[PDB]
Amino acid sequence: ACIESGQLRLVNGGGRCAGRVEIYHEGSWGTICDDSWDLSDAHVVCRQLGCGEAINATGSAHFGEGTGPIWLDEMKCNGKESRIWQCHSHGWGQQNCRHKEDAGVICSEFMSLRLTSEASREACAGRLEVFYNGAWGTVGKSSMSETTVGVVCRQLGCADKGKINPA
Amino acid sequence: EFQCEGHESHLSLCPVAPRPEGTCSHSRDVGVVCSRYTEIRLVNGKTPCEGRVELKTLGAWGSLCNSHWDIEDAHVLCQQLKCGVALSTPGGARFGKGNGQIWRHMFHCTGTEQHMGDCPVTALGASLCPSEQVASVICSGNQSQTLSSCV
Ligand SMILES: [Ca+2]
Ligand SMILES: [Ca+2]
Ligand SMILES: [Ca+2]
């Protein structure tokens, strides 16, 4: 019944499950070194947040530089665990990698919405694609209220209102 | 692995980042070359604070020349010897006779430096040293005298 400590806070991803990983240990927020970052290592971090399995594991903190101190280094893991700290660790707190080597992980569901035409990858009129489990798919036609379209246009940032073209 | 910042007075005052156990082979050990590179000893002197000045290079001993030899070079030589600065510079060869091979090195030193190897040395192309003009020194022996800007 606590907020607890050491929760893998994912930020800069734009969703609930994406971006860099941050850990609040000994009262300090910190990133994770990318030394020998493994996809099997990315499986546990996704499971702890309840997101699911892992799709990609990215290094060099391309999601974003982490200002905080580096906490763990050279983490490898069996991939089947519930507590992140219980992963094969070369010690604690001491790192051979500096910042710009922070780790990033994409979990099972980081959904992205795009408006696509043949000419433009992102345009303001076209088809509706949804990102799920590292894949792109069309959206259903049946039972679309005017409010349903209204939200899609607002999220994509094209217009306040929108309309369905039959063509 | 050392991580010294550069201004440490000693190596023991250095942040050390110890990698886990594991080493390279013995063939990859390192060696450093500091700039002192010169050995000066007083020879044929009745007391330790004075003697004929010799420097060793190319695996041989030879005496310095009084030509282009001034008082401050004796002073900094004394400071290295820790006898205290030379009260007076001896003239001629009153106690230096030997080592017919004479190095022509002449030392241009301001005297502020503490070790005579530090002050710049130019010797390439120097003219031949006349005989009996071998340099020397007569240090104070007080050990309580220090150089001062301007006896
Ligand atoms: Ca790295
Ligand atoms: Ca690993
Ligand atoms: Ca390392």
Image: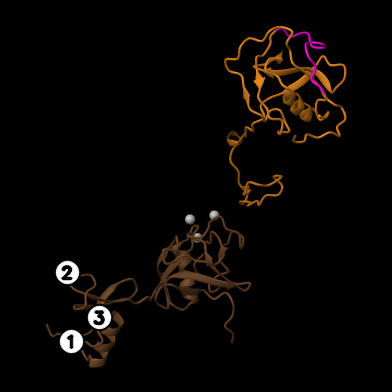
Chain colours: A brown, B orange
Mark 1, residues whose alpha carbon is within 10 Å: few (<14), some, or many (≥20)? few
SS at circle 2: loop
Q: Quadrant of residue B123?
A: top right
Above-or-below relation of A24 to A101 = below
Tell me, yes or no, whether dots 2 and 1 are on the same chain.
yes
Residue at the spot 88% in from the left edge and 30% down from the top edge:
B142
Do the residues under discs 3 and 1 have CB atoms within 8 angstroms?
A: no
Residue A19 is situated, as x and y percent measured from the top left of the image, at 43, 70
- The quadrant in which the N terminus of chain A is found is bottom right
Report the amino acid beneath label 3: Cys
In the rendered image, residue B96 lying in the magenta stretch gets the answer yes
Label 1 belongs to which residue? Answer: A164
The answer as to whether the residues below labels 3 and 1 share one chain is yes
The magenta region covers B88-100
Query: Which x, y percent locates residue B40?
Result: 73, 22
Q: Which element carries disc 1, helix, strand or loop?
A: loop
**Image quadrant where residue B94 sits:** top right
Question: Under 8 Å from ligand 2: the CB of mark 1?
Answer: no
Which of the two residues, A121 or B11, is positioned nearer the viewer here? B11
**Seen in the image, is B91 located left or right of residue B24?**
right
Residue drawn at point x = 61 percent, y = 51 percent: B19
Q: Residues within 10 Å of mark 3 (few under 14, many from 20)?
A: some
In the visual, does B5 lie left or right of A135?
right
Relative horizontal placement of residue A102, taking residue A3 as reference (left or right): left
Q: Which label's residue is closer to the chain start, 2 or 1?
A: 2
Q: Single out the residue that lies furthest toward the front.
A: B150
The answer to whether mark 2 and mark 1 are in CB contact below 8 A is no
Q: Which mark is residue A119?
A: 2
Point out which mark residue A158 bears.
Answer: 3
